[PDB]
Amino acid sequence: LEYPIGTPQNLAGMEIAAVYLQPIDMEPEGHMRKASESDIHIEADIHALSNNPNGYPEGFWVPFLFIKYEITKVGGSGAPITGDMMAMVASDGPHYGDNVKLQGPGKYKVKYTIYPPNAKENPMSPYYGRHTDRETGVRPWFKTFSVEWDFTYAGI
Amino acid sequence: LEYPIGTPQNLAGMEIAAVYLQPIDMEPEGHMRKASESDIHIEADIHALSNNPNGYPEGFWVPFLFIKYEITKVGGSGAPITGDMMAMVASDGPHYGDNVKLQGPGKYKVKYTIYPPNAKENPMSPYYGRHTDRETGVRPWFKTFSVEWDFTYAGI
Ligand SMILES: [Cu+]
Ligand SMILES: [Cu+]
Ligand SMILES: [Fe+3]
Ligand SMILES: [Fe+3]
Ligand SMILES: [Fe+3]
Ligand SMILES: [Fe+3]
Image 1 (tube, chains in turn yellow, orange):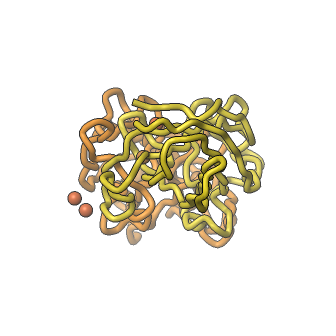
Image 2 (cartoon, chains in turn red, blue; image 1 turned 30 degrees about the vertical axis):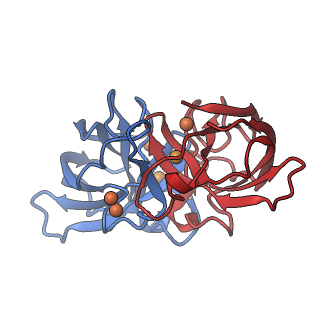
């Protein structure tokens, strides 16, 4: 089962939603924190809106992005939980996610930093292209942006 | 306007169609053969079918694949034209494609070799995951396969 973190935010011709669930098992092994050592599996569900400037039809998953997360416990006496999400596929389709260990129940601040395919930070920069010619060309990639939400962790 | 290469073939829970159009200009530069040095831009349009075993909803583009192509001129006294396609986005959405120089008008044989994200040959093996756990898990990736077509090049 999936639990939402705030309401989805629409930016750069995309709908950015943040959900969480029980920790997961993934292939290749050694990328995700072990489920037994994790608290949640945090996800970034990024999908195209109508008239997306980079050629994606409505509802399509936006691939080859790189998402960095920052999770801070509201009022908590702990450091921010940071990490990088990974592109993966599940029963609900492709998404960006990571297995995370939290700092107990309470209110938390979540911040995602979405990097375009051409970003200096994006390892998949040389693997994904964009047509520029008049006939089949699309608009330049969006510039790196951040997105925040507040959520109450109860303990799932 | 795109021109078709035979009829699409349905394999491994996907619909595999081969098209071509005029050569393109792509960002980043230095990956595609120059449009002035090319004859066509060959594409592989791979989309999910209903009941796709790896979690893709119907119509969705299948990402992180690696496609190798082999183009032979029927009866022609020329070497086969080979290469690797690249994941890119255009006005019609994401796909795999490459700029190719043909050997004049005539009948041709096209052969694509589709590699799953976990393939030894696929550079994007450490970049794309798959849930394996009972609840959110999907079926293992398809095994590497080939698809062939015959087409008549008239000259764009
Ligand atoms: Cu995931
Ligand atoms: Cu292309
Ligand atoms: Fe393994
Ligand atoms: Fe294993
Ligand atoms: Fe999800
Ligand atoms: Fe196309």
